[PDB]
Image (cartoon, rainbow over all chains, first blue to last red; front, side, top):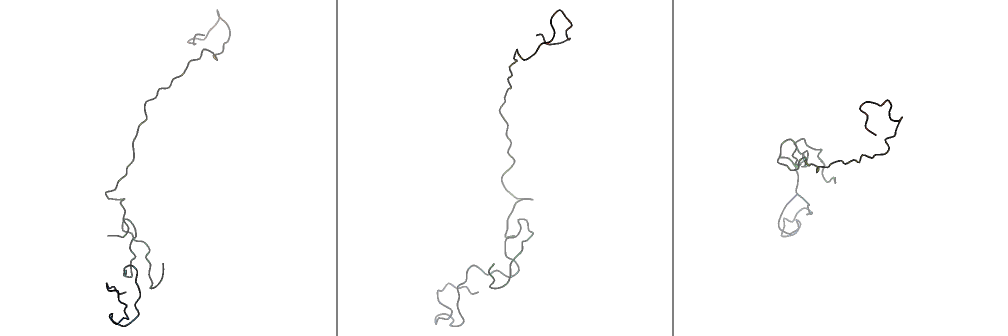
Length: 54
Length: 53
């Protein structure tokens, strides 16, 4: 995941000009937790894997 | 902190148990002179403390 404010493709001459540039949705979350679990801290069941849509 | 929020054990939440009362009401009953039946006659043995009929 790469974040940039310039609307230039990663393979373009203006960009680094290497690799394939793909649109990324949302922010990257470190593998271990998924966020909302328990009102009082108990923790829910998180999700893992890369590319997996769940 | 936690992603999920809740206030059960200790938190500044709202809502409580409502308390209310009903307006005073009076029960009115009519003492009908009929339907009391009759047994025997007069001049005769009568139950003590019986209602006069």
